[PDB]
Image (cartoon, rainbow, N blue to C red):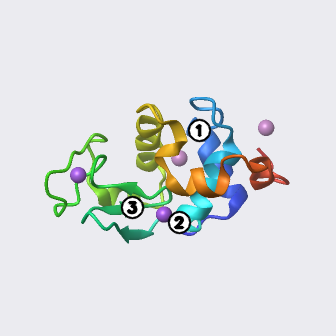
Amino acid sequence: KVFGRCELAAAMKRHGLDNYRGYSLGNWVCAAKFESNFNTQATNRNTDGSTDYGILQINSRWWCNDGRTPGSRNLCNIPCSALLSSDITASVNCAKKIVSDGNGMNAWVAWRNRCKGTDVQAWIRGCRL
Ligand code: NA
Ligand code: NA
Ligand SMILES: [Rh+]
Ligand SMILES: [Rh+]
């Protein structure tokens, strides 16, 4: 599923991300835009052999089991395929554990490089929330 900007903002707010660990909703929308272009089906291979899945590009090195990442963990206790659903529940619940892991949203290299220190409120401007 390819979300609209405001549709994804509303789904993220309904699932508890607005100000989660102090990150405003625009941060999460900005991260999703640069990670997946709001596409739940997005997949990308990493140099280490792990893969990033879904709207927030959650990695198989730590967070999910894809059956092909050796010496990895599954800290969200999910198959990676769950992160590709039109229903963003698994991605949201796994993002909350990631952002709680010590480095905040710096866990998402795209957030640190494209959203941190920018006017992220712009990502939710005009949305009925
Ligand atoms: Na990415
Ligand atoms: Na894994
Ligand atoms: Rh939902
Ligand atoms: Rh509202």
- Measured from the top left, where is residue 1 in percent x and y? 52, 68
Q: How far apart are the two marked residues, 2 and 3, measured between alpha carbons?
A: 9 Å
The structure residue drawn at horizontal position 78% and vertical position 47%, both measured from the top left corner, is 121
Q: Is residue 27 left or right of residue 127?
A: left
Residue corresponding to mark 1: 17
Q: Is residue 1 above or below residue 123?
A: below
**Disc 3 residue type (three-letter):** Tyr
Instruction: Please tell me in which quarter of the rendered image ligand 4 is found.
Output: top right
Residue corresponding to mark 3: 53
**Which type of secondary structure does the marked residue at label 2 adopt?**
helix
**Which type of secondary structure does the marked residue at label 1 adopt?**
loop
Residue corresponding to mark 2: 36
- Measured from the top left, where is residue 56 in percent x and y? 49, 55
**Disc 1 residue type (three-letter):** Leu
Q: How many marks?
A: 3
Q: Is residue 127 left or right of residue 19?
A: right
Badge 1: residue crowd in 10 Å (few <14, some 14–19, many ≥20): many
Q: How far apart are the two marked residues, 1 and 2, measured between alpha carbons?
A: 17 Å
Does the closest atom of ligand 2 sit within 8 Å of the Cβ of label 3? no
The structure residue drawn at horizontal position 23% and vertical position 60%, both measured from the top left corner, is 66
Q: Quadrant of residue 45?
A: bottom left
Tell me the quarter of the image containing the C terminus. top right
- Marks 1 & 3, CB-CB < 8 Å contact: no
**Residue 8 seen in render:** no
**Disc 2 residue type (three-letter):** Ser
- Marks 2 & 3, CB-CB < 8 Å contact: no
